[PDB]
Amino acid sequence: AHYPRPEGCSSPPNAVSVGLHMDLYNYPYLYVKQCWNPEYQDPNFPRYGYKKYGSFGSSDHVNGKISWDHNEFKEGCKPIMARLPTAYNYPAKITFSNFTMVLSGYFKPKSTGLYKFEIHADDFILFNFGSKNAFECCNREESIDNFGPYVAYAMWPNEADQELEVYLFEDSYYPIRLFYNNRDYHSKFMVGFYPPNTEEITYDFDGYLYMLDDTGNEC
Ligand SMILES: OC[C@H]1O[C@@H](O[C@H]2[C@H](O)[C@@H](O)[C@H](O)O[C@@H]2CO)[C@H](O)[C@@H](O)[C@H]1O
Ligand SMILES: [Ca+2]
Ligand SMILES: [Cl-]
Image (cartoon, rainbow, N blue to C red; front, side, top):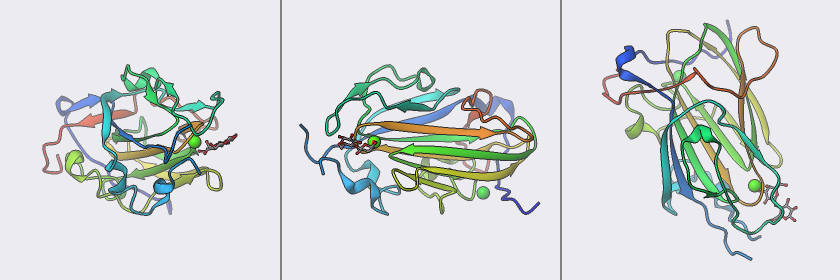
């Protein structure tokens, strides 16, 4: 009714594959054993600053249980090696203590209705969603950094939990861009949702995440 109703994309099944694309970028400490770099707080970081230390990895077909909560680490101010969930199809350990990730692709609802998303961050998550907010239909790679004002901005410690509601249509693939940073130590990337008429949250995206071919012409 008076809920946000973002725009989505159409494609035939033959131009559709399963899962999101991931890029991983370096985020160094200032020094290693204010050890951590405050750069991630800069207003320009999400749009272009985040690539300035180079990339180190990528994957495709990211699907299913994409959230994590690593609060087992014992030492701060120190790179700590650990593995991403198996959802990411990325075998190597990463500097889990300090890194930047961009996840992008399309969310397709299994039914038409109001979806509520919830994010919980350590350190930083940005949520863009819709063809007029995240990126253009079938032009993801070129338009990935042309995102608009955030649908959710979650930052540790003071704004770490956020939520948003979007009314979505079964037939539509919605551009989604999820940005994550860890500056130091513990790492939480929790992105879940409540489908229509559903009380319990889920962190399993299986059957909701897709990629469309970048053929350009609004598909
Ligand atoms: O509490 C999560 C928070 O930790 C910060 O690091 C602190 C840590 O909490 C503290 O126990 C330890 O003794 O000092 C650390 C400083 O390195 C992280 O900087 C922050 O990103 C959060 O993960
Ligand atoms: Ca952290
Ligand atoms: Cl939109």
